[PDB]
Amino acid sequence: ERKMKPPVQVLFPIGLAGGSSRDIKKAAEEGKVAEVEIAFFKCPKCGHVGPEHLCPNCGTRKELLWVCPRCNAEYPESQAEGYNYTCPKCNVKLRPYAKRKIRPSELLNRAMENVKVYGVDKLKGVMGMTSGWKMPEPLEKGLLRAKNDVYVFKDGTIRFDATDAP
Amino acid sequence: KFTHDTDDIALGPKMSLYKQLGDMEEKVRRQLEVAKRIRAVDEHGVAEKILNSHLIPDLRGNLRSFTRQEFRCVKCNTKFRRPPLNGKCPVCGGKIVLTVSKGAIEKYLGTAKMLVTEYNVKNYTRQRICLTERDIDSLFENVFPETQLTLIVNPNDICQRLVMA
Amino acid sequence: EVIGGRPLFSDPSKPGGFRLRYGRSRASGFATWGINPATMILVDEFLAIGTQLKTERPGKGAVVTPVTTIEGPIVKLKDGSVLRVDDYNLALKVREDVEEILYLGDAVIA
Amino acid sequence: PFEIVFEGAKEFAQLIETASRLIDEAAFKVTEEGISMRAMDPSRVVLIDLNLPASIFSKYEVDGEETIGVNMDHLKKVLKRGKAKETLILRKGEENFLEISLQGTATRTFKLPLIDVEEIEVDLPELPFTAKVVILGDVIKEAVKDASLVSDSMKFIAKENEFTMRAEGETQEVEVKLTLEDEGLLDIEVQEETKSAYGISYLSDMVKGLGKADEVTIKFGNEMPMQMEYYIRDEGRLIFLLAPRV
Amino acid sequence: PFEIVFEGAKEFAQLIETASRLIDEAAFKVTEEGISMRAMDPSRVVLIDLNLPASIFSKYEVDGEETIGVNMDHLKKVLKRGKAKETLILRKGEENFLEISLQGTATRTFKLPLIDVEEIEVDLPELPFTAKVVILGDVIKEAVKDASLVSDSMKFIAKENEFTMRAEGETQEVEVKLTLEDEGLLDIEVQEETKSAYGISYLSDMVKGLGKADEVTIKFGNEMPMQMEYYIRDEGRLIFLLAPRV
Amino acid sequence: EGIVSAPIEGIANVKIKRNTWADNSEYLALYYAGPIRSSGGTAQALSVLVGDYVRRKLGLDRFKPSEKHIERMVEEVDLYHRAVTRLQYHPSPEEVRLAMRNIPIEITGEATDDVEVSHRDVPGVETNQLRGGAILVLAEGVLQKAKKLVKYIDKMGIEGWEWLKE
Amino acid sequence: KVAKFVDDLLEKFYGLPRFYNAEKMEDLIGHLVIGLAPHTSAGIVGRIIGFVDALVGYAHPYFHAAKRRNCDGDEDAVMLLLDALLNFSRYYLPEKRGGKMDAPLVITTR
Amino acid sequence: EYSKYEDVVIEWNPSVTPVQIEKNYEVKFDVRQVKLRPPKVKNGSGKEGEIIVEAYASLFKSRLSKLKRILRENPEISNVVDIGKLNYVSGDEEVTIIGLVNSKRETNRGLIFEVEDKTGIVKVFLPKDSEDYREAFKVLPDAVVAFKGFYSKKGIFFANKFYLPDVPLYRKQKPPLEEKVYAILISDIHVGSREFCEKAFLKFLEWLNGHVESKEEEEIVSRVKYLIIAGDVVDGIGIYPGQYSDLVIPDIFDQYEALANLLANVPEHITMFIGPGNADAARPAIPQPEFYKEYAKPIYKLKNAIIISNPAVIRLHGRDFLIAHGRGIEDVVSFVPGLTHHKPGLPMVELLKMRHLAPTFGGKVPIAPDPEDLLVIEEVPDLVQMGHVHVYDAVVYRGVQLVNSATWQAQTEFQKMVNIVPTPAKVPVVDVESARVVKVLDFSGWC
DNA sequence: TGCACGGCTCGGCCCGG
DNA sequence: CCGGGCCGAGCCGTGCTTT
Ligand SMILES: [Mg+2]
Ligand SMILES: [Mg+2]
Ligand SMILES: [Mg+2]
Ligand SMILES: [Zn+2]
Ligand SMILES: [Zn+2]
Ligand SMILES: [Zn+2]
């Protein structure tokens, strides 16, 4: 099989909170707070904010938030579309990500309640996302991969490497 | 179409023996036995010499990186091109570790000496190995002095024999 | 160059090495060779189905594949006898008594 | 073929484990007199000899003398499954398999393949030992454990009516002194002033495993090897040869 | 030049081990009445006070006064080398070496180099303490061990004839309640209700290694550091002050 | 045939430069990234030929290198082989000089190795480190696979490449 | 294991019926995979018809050539079609130059 | 084909008789003269991974403490303060800091340093308009410098002066001699190579024995008394891959035997001082105590040969000679733009100014893990000899003469590849009294 | 062609004082 | 019963070179 240089089961950044093995579960169980760069999405109706694609309160799709690198002003995707992805008050091109704070305990508990998979010992993530969007992966997929003993690749697929013969 | 037929398409050994040998000395010994059995290989002078031209680069290239190496902290990942003169990481409390250890230079020295003493190699390679050993034991002259005596000496070595001859 | 642990099976164009046969088997032809399993066994199983090797004449590199229709090695036993090991089971049986491999076998090349 | 049974298999396991701390491959010389062993460590720094006469064997039958060579690690791993209240039985047939049996509340049989090792004869003449000191195991073990804190070399000084051991580090100092008036020494016989030094790793490796109620005698001199003995089951004996420092 | 003799070195080593888990280097002031030490946490979060009057020691001879600066690790190792019934003697001569001599079956001696360490003399007089409770060391040790599982924060609650310590987490919750009818709460003097919180790492560090038959005294108040003190040999005592969190 | 990712990865950028040192005339340059080393000799040589044809059809002049450029490129090739990889091909310095003298485009790129060169501050070059992609292209493309390249030239009816045929 | 993970994903995260329903490796026969060389950006769809007891991937010579491979030492990848369809995304691709290699940005059907 | 100068014989010319001169000399420095105590571990069971780090740190400590004492000699330097206690100084005071140069960047305003000492790291800025800004622009790291200026509570230490250990401007002239004495310098003989030109060396050996052409040369030859060789006396074995085809004598024992046979032809009144180099059988990293005795015995057996170390200082008639090989020049050439191998005098003067023969660690020079730094020039010499660059040069700097003796190996394939031009068979002659080069011989006609 | 080798830390279990 | 000694996973770094 194909595994990254440190093995990874979900494409979710944890930083230094998880330790050497980037264990999301160990950081969550100790109540640590991690500071990393991710993409935050915001629900248009009520106003939930966090690294998720669906709002738990109402189950409606959120919108990516654009941040100003100089003044940290947040705009929804619809608003930034008119602004040509440039800050009007400032003058700098926006970015979809910023360095933020996350509490792994709430996210992991929500995921476990979502997929009804409670008995998992380890769950490895990444130190930092390498993309330009820094969009994370759902944690439910990581939980199911950990449960079924499979590993992820740089684009989200599971691959097997073998020699070829005719 | 095809020319030759086969009874079974997956008949024969399935795993290479190279993946079941642990030590380097064991690998070299098994490979030399295999070369000795086959009539048309002529191990005794070309196999061992061409093999020695694979461990010699490792030896010489690891002694030249010990004298110009960068140090690093165990907790941090900070790399210092020269060691901190207080003995500890300036930005934390951890201790400093080498990036090229002393045992990385002389991991292939025993197999190289066996290859030199057992088989027929030109005197160039034999002298290179003897001088490499002498140079390895001379760089640490005043950091690791030989303060330990011994009961029995002369284990049929080759370097001392070459020197006394 | 020879790496430690990777044997050399024949000197350049030396009689007693691999015998050249022109042809293509069921599972060879693109860039792969055809090898009898008996000579896979009688080299201490360093060769296995799919193991690469650096060749001399046609190109540089190939993958080995079993072909039982061609000849195998001729070996000299410990008591002085000579045998033609063209069979897989015979190679398994007589492996421990081998003293010298007189001939190494064939190699089908397209 | 032979049959050997021993009482208190835990003591035999401890002895084999102590032997295993320095050497890896060794062969046993079983004869009509008993069984004996001798080997040298790969670094050629320590030499261990040990014999077990028939006196300490409850039952012992043999057709003569034979050499048996087994892997030490596997032997001690098997021996460590025993208990202090079980009997150990060693048996071998014409086949090259060493059958080991432990008889307690049940009977279990272990099969260990044999191996061949070079039985080179290594021996040395009786060197001139000017000083001899007999002390308990506990005192020397404690002295070694204190010495290990500060340095890696331990120094001996033997004087008439005064035997002392020292271990000095870079800035810290450790010293142990005793006399025959004290309770830690049995007897001392020195012919002149003696000074020597030996490493801490080897000393800790060999001294470890000695009971408190053991009489250990040490023979050493000036810049010359050291010899240590302790009696086993009141009939046997063990030797340790250690090369000096500097 | 002073000579101080102590009996039962194990208790001394245990006390030094508890005192050495907060600061690495501390200074001891030897004076006729006794030895007193007041260190400071490197992060400035917990206070530790030492007081060892001359009444405990069997022999106590000293003239004038002197400060003794030593690093905790070497002294802790030397003391932990002491066995159950080893007499502990502390002696300093004209030299700059702090001699630790141990007496028993053998005379084992250690030496340490004194280190110059700055002294920060900050005396804290009596503070307004809302409540004072004395409980057995077993109860607090067990309660801290149980609360270490759920979270990293302990909440102390004291009321009229009621002592309650609680820890809360994301999902789990642990609470221990005590009252006069239990064998742990010896008595409780409280003028008014108070509540405060403290860290679990520091609490475990201070509370670890406390004997079961110890009348540990706890005094604390609303949003105010807790004071803890227990007696040693009916004459000596150790005092802990831990700053609160949030 | 649109399978290997040379057009997507190897060609980092295409820019137009002026011969300020000789005539102030314009020409075309190609920037090769790291991934071009995995494309293959045929892909690299075909990229060079396509660049030549596009420069011809855009009405642009020829790259006119100074001698210092030739010295810098020879030193770059030698040092890259000495300190990085075997290159599976050894161009003699005469071949390198001939290739530089007879290529109508500028083959350059970013730095891919942490080694400095001697001939620094060359005009038209914005780096002083090894250009692994460009030199690997020049070594294992037009030089290692000149037979297939001249076959393609003959099939393609392209003039100006007679030096390669010779 | 990959098929079990896909079935769990479909049943739990998305609320759809299972697809593979396999208990032994022989229950994957007739299902489709994707072959991908480590230096290309397009894949090719293949079908499983059997299993062998060797450490090689046997396939037609046209299958290996359509991935620009030579079959003398090369190694490629296979992944289940549905896994790649559900999981692959272009927003997880690194932003350096060598980030679009090994990615199935398009697949060939014939 | 195994000629090794077996039967080469050169006899003294009876037409000329040497004059009588008292042989007053002594070796003032040798690496196998300082007893370096090995460092002990911080605990009882230390291992290999910490003793090496401790030894390197102790070496750097010794370097800093040795080069700090030299700086505080000229009265112009005063008010030295500890770097650690810089937060307790007023903003109107003038202070000096001494430490190691970690790094040196360049900005539009000037240069920024990372000076570090025993008690912490401090940043330093030097304005572009400073009078000494030119000197500090081309200093390479790990050297010991002094900075003078005003400290700020906001970090950066603004400075207006820059100091190097340097060489004093004033010195007292030594008393003269009763008669003149001459000495000769040679380096990089490279015995056993194909590009080594033996005929030129035989002609030179003939020249030393009285085979002269002019009266003044005859007078000099009759007066010569000493001879110093500065490394690379044999081509060595296994220096680079593919050297076997480049060797005429592919045996290190035979290389040293042939070299010994060649040098035996000099008159017995000439005393050799031989030092090892980077191609001999000697220590992999500098300083090198000596040759490997079991490999270089024939050159030890020479009757008039005295084997010295690298670096070593020799005193002849009260004149100090700092004899070194010169592996440290390559770092100076690489780091400071505007210098080339063809002119090694300027890099040598820079090394003399810094008072260290190989400042930077981790570059092109291998530094051994010693507890004491022996490469610092403690005492200022009268003459300095070097080699390793195969190019002749000579300069004078504040009274001391800096000489770079040439090679005897003709240009090889590699030196052609890297565009290096050797100047073989050039030999400088030095007068003992003035410690200055007075004549340069040339035997390049044969080579 | 890149993998193969050394070293440091950090818990989970015995086993013994 | 409570405290060490020890294994077994993991995670980092490194592999000829003339002046
Ligand atoms: Mg291929
Ligand atoms: Mg030279
Ligand atoms: Mg040299
Ligand atoms: Zn919502
Ligand atoms: Zn803004
Ligand atoms: Zn650190």
Image (cartoon, coloured by chain):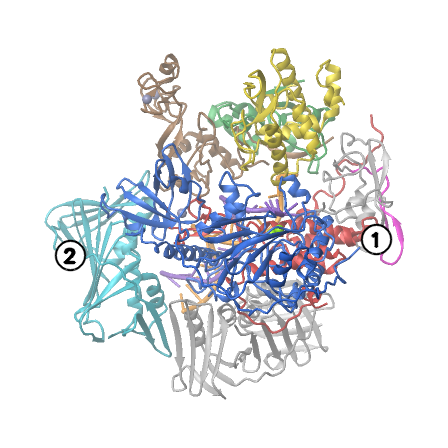
Chain colours: A brown, B red, E cyan, F yellow, G green, H blue, I orange, J purple
Residue B3 coordinates in the image, percent (x, y) = 85, 30
Q: Quadrant of the N terminus of chain B?
A: top right
Same subunit, tags 1 and 2:
no
Residue at image point 33% right, 64% down:
E76
Q: Look at label 1 and name its amino acid.
A: Glu
> Which chain is indicated by disc 1?
C
Residue lying furthest left in this view? Answer: E191
Quadrant for the C terminus of chain B, please.
bottom right
Farthest front residue in view: H215
Residue H109 spot, x, y in % from top left: 36, 33
Residue matched to label 2? E123
Q: CA distance from mark 1 to mark 2?
A: 91 Å
Give x and y (percent) for residue A142: 47, 33
| Residue C24 among those drawn in magenta | no
What is the magenta segment's predominant secondary structure? loop
Bin the neighbour count of mark 2 within 10 Å (Cα to Cα): few under 14, some 14-19, many 20 and up. few
Q: Which residues are magenta?
A: C66-85
Task: Determine whether the residue tagged by mark 1 lies in a helix, strand or loop.
Answer: strand
Cβ of disc 1 within 8 Å of ligand 1? no
Foreground pick, C4 / F147: F147
Mark 1: give few (<14), some (14-19) or many (20+) Cα within 10 Å.
some
Check residue C67 for magenta coloring: yes
Q: Is residue B66 visible?
A: no
Work out whether C60 lies above or below F11. below
Q: Is residue C49 above or below residue A75?
A: below
Chain label for disc 2: E
Could you say where residue G74 lies in the image, as x and y percent from the top left?
68, 33
Given residues H294 and A32, the one toward you in this image is H294
